Amino acid sequence: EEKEKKENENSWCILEHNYEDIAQEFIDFIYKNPTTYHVVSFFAELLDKHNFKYLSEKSNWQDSIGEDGGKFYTIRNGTNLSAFILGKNWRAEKGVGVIGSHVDALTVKLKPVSFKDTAEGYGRIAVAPYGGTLNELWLDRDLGIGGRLLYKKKGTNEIKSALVDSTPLPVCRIPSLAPHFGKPAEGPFDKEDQTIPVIGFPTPEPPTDDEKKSPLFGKHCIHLLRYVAKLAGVEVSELIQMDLDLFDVQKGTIGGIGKHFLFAPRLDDRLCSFAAMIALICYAKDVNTEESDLFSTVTLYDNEEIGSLTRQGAKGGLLESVVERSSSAFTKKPVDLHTVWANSIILSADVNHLYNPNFPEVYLKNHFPVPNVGITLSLDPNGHMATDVVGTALVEELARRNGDKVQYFQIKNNSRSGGTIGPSLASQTGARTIDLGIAQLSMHSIRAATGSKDVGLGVKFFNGFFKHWRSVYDEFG
Amino acid sequence: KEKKENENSWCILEHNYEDIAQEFIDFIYKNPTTYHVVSFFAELLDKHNFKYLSEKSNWQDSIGEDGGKFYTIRNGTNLSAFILGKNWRAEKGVGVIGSHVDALTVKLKPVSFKDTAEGYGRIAVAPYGGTLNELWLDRDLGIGGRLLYKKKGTNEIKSALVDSTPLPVCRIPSLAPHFGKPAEGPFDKEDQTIPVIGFPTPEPPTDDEKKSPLFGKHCIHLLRYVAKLAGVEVSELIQMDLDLFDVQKGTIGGIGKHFLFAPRLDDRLCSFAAMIALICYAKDVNTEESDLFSTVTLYDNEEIGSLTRQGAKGGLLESVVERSSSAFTKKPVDLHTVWANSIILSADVNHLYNPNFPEVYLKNHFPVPNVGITLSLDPNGHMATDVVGTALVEELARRNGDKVQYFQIKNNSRSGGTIGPSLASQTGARTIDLGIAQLSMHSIRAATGSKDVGLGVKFFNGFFKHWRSVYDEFG
Amino acid sequence: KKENENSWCILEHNYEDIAQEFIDFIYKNPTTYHVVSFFAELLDKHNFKYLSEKSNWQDSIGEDGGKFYTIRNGTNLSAFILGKNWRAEKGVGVIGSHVDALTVKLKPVSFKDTAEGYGRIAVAPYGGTLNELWLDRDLGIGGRLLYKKKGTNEIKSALVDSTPLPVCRIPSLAPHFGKPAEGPFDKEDQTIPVIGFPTPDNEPPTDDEKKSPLFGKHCIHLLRYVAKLAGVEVSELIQMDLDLFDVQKGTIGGIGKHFLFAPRLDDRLCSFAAMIALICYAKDVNTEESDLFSTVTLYDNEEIGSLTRQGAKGGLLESVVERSSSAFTKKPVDLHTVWANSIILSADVNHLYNPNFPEVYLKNHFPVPNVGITLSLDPNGHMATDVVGTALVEELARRNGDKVQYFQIKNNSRSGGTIGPSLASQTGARTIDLGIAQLSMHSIRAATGSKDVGLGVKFFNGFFKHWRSVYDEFG
Ligand SMILES: C[As](C)(=O)[O-]
Ligand SMILES: C[As](C)(=O)[O-]
Ligand SMILES: C[As](C)(=O)[O-]
Ligand SMILES: C[As](C)(=O)[O-]
Ligand SMILES: C[As](C)(=O)[O-]
Ligand SMILES: C[As](C)(=O)[O-]
Ligand SMILES: [Zn+2]
Ligand SMILES: [Zn+2]
Ligand SMILES: [Zn+2]
Ligand SMILES: [Zn+2]
Ligand SMILES: [Zn+2]
Ligand SMILES: [Zn+2]
């Protein structure tokens, strides 16, 4: 009972040097929450279990947050979440300790009309890529279906939503052509005409009159509508709309001959999102908000893989909104947000690239990370990352204090860089922003890899950030 | 009787789609530049009892507890009209239609002067967006836009709009195919697609005309002409912002009159439909009794990416809502709560199925003429439309008796972007990309359905009436 | 006193002194850090009070207004003068420029193994550097060191500069070797700075030196060198952000001394000219009497797209005006009214006519040396300049006795973009892109007219004196 509670804290927050348990919780998390909707829902439920109070965006917060502050979260669009801890003794000059990550991952979306005519008896579905999917890595993979259904119960005018998930059933697969056929079997393949998921081969019930009353009748195969309705526990007639993903249902696993690796889908950026959220929860356990003088948050964004210019992406400003609304409700007096942000540190936590020993020519000597060491700073002099000399120094100081190791990633001068939310958050807030993350192999694959210790090592680092960033940043004044 | 007949034609109350189609054609023809379009809507708003508010003055003394019907203009090319009900509160949100009034055109260069070329007069021009291609060759081009002038013996700089219509002052002449390879396009936009304005025979500049700041920057024939159109002296002209545009008047067409052919549909088609819908809706709205905040905001510079003060990224919508709500309550307004409860229709024209290019249209995701409004859907952020917005629009249409169509690109194709994503992130409000579909977007002369203007007006009117009620189903 | 004012502020037609001060400024302040520090020291000497971003400005700015400046990141500076009689309807008179220039940055780990005895350092390009123009140039090293004195927990900053010593040179391969000596060259493997060729008798690292966080990240000779320049121990070094730059001092040139040759003109030329205009202007402003709000805001990261906290998109201008106006009045300020009445000059260098490349310059739309400020015009959103802005600057010039030139690209050419569109969009204010024209933009060593620095200062000084009065004629 009491020993199990101590052992639980030790596993989740790596207090007894137990990295294996947190690695498995991450794997289970990825497997049980295939879509962005599931991930945000998982964290929402996690936050409820650790006494964070949900606040709706749709209502003013002046009545919900008082002088004692506390632990809160809000959700936008079901895909964009911000959790935060506000201290009774917080002032504008203390700033905010932020970790910003994204919860969207490369996937395949069902088209608004997924219906395709049968092709020599084969059932197929019309889909679209979200980011750079539907390539050769997506061929011959077991694909489940899941996401958000919108429904309206009979004899009501309420539109409600349900999350669905076929796991472990792979409902479809994108079949490669056998190499025996020659040149037609050689990639790359047309994302509209060639990489189409095969969902069935049915044999010889037709649609009922009630099923035909569904808004989605004609838009999707009657078998599909029946299936998702059964998963949701509603009638076909009640289905209003849907937003469904196809995703790899292969469960993650520890691997390598010495178990040094973790293989799993959708690491970018659910890896950092998970580690940052668990760190927040671990940190929150020992925070009395009545005595604290800090403002801490993890904010999770959608649509980072498509450039962040949506209301649920980093450019939509959920962070800025949360800090403005909370501080207004907290003090009930004029808060200078420019002073707030000038004293803040934002960690833009996004996965970066582990050294791949089979492609040494793309990695910059002395500026790549390796597995199971620690967090990696993303450095770039051309604005792809927001990291600057003070932020580098802050993180290195933090790590030396907390016993963490820090690695570097920067591109070769003849190479090219990805871009993160970091520059966007820095510009929108005016606050010093540091791009960093847990490094991984095979980013944007359907199944990626990181170190087996790296989930725990990330949790450890981010926990130390929340504990010590304010004290460390004060050295620079 | 006359007022009942006008309401039927303009607001499609008696099922009359012909008249509103003709008014749209007349509107496009009579207002060739963005300046003219904004001026048209300003005059229209004045006639329906909307009060102009200047951006340069604080609105607290102009808007009170009763709210009302208002509009404002930035740069002469960015206009926001709004209806603020006396019983509005932050949790009601705002119902917004955002469209753009800029269209592909050709601009006179700051110095339009060119030396005569074997006797031919020509003017130096620049493309605004993807113009000066083969579709702009051999078209009758009028000249028009904004002149800035200063009356002689005064210091004030004033504005006049000018328009040569029906006179086409110039034409970009194709080379006869007889000459062979030189006559094959594409053509150089600087050296080959140059408007020919005249061929003058053997008065030189007077001493007064030389006092013009524009003397030497434009041909004296041109300066005299635009001076005459504005009713000012050449000496008084300080600057100008002039377009060249197709003066071919729009028309109903097709063997069964199913089509409307007209220039500059992108996006004056949705802008007109949304604005007429707002005026129709406003006729039956008592602002003393209303609990809603409704707006149509019209932007400039969308075709060049919206990053100007008069484009979507310049934030006129957000400013209007902030200034209105501060003046209205005279107390702190939670603008985050306002936008969280809002719906933005990003109304921009999308693509009708072209039966001659079936390979670029996505099966089950193309619109056809004369059916209804088309949702623009995109999973990679080119459009702001999401699952809830789709369901909302479909719910709204089922209630109002409208039809809804889909547009989405093929996976192996390419998509343009709209202001929708910009508005969504700037406000944090759910934004829905949709519009009236058309053929031949970005041509000098495009086409849509002859009923689509009226169908568009009907849908947007339905939006203003029922969006709040329908969106409450999702809460 | 009068001789100093006449030299700096060009009051007795002395253009050579200010040109030489500019050359000295460029030579003594090679990095963005030095440039901001130079302007900070200049502002201090002219009685502008420094305000930290990290504290509320309520206790530093009162109803009297005054002369102030603030700094973000050591590279983003905003200086401003706020009049006691200022109100929202007077707006703000803004010059916005950038102080970052194309350079070469040391990598976070600059260490390289010796290569047949040669010492080299690992570096990266900031903008389009490490090309053939960067070969065979004498390169100095300088920038910001972070250190922590022994027995303290205080991270402090020091600026270092090797000038006149060129520590580095990127050596071209001799043409004798043939094809390998033909560019372009790989920026990672071929354009690597050579820093030395050490001999055995450069001592081994001491135990204290090994305690540095930077031990292993840079070779010990480099660490010892930068420690000696800052006056600290190697062990105390925490981090560094260092540039490589041309140490060739600028000069007046041409057979008639019509030119000025110097490195890093983009955009320290306009920044210097704008800042000196502000100080010259500020000498005769009594803030107790003034009703104006004036600012020069200097940005970092313009050359890489401005999307950082210290770039234009980070909003230091907007922040300055909001914080100032809040502390100034303590009765709420309508910022939308403020910006609606404002003028922003986006002052960034544009392109002088290069007579060797006539084919890329647009006839009647290029500037020449020693005439005056050049308006940057573009109808596709690369610049923010509009017809009213053009007329304002021309009016202003006519009143102050300045000359104005034009720059616009040919229809078949390509344009760069400035911060102008960003600033116009973020504020909603009318923004005018203009600048002092130069040859050879983005070279390691560029050129402008020898009179153009003074002509720039004179024009910008005229702007601060007269912009409010002139813009009132357009109302
Ligand atoms: C050669 As193919 C278009 O079938 O990948
Ligand atoms: C766009 As990314 C840095 O999540 O691969
Ligand atoms: C070959 As050509 C420039 O006359 O279209
Ligand atoms: C830039 As567009 C969607 O108006 O063609
Ligand atoms: C031809 As080479 C890559 O040595 O510049
Ligand atoms: C990006 As630029 C207009 O300073 O060359
Ligand atoms: Zn990614
Ligand atoms: Zn990522
Ligand atoms: Zn368009
Ligand atoms: Zn459009
Ligand atoms: Zn530049
Ligand atoms: Zn520049």
Image (cartoon, coloured by chain):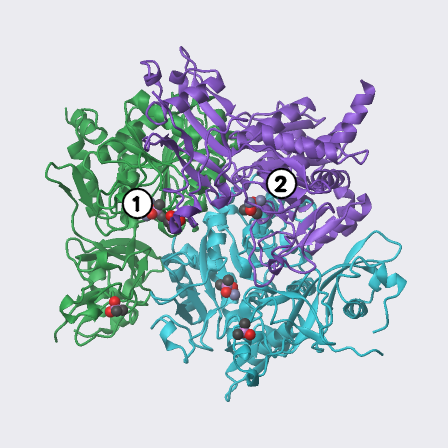
Chain colours: A purple, B green, C cyan
- Res. C79 in view: yes
| Residue at the far bottom in the pictured view | C255
Residue B297 in the image: state x and y as whole percent.
Answer: 37, 39
Q: Does the residue tagged 2 have its C-beta within 8 Å of any atom of ligand 8?
A: no
Vertical relation: C384 (above or below) A88: below
Quadrant for residue A277, please give it. top right
Q: Which residue is mark 1?
A: B360
Vertical relation: C470 (above or below) A432: below
Instruction: Inspect the image, locate mark 1, and give the three-letter code of the amino acid beneath it.
Output: Val
Give A109 or A159, whichever is nearer the viewer: A109
Mark 2, secondary structure of its residue: strand
Question: How many tags in the picture?
Answer: 2
Residue A5 left/right relative to C28: right
Give C264 or B145, whichever is nearer the viewer: C264
Residue A263 in the image: state x and y as whole percent.
Answer: 63, 39
Chain label for disc 2:
A
Residue C45 left/right relative to C376: right
- Res. C465 in view: no
Chain label for disc 1:
B
Give A444 or A43, whichever is nearer the viewer: A444
**Residue at screen point 17% across, 77% down:** B118
Mark 1, secondary structure of its residue: helix
Quadrant for residue A361, please give it. bottom right
**Residue at screen point 65% across, 27% down:** A72
Instruction: Inspect the image, locate mark 2, and give the three-letter code of the amino acid beneath it.
Output: Gly
Q: Which residue is mark 2?
A: A100
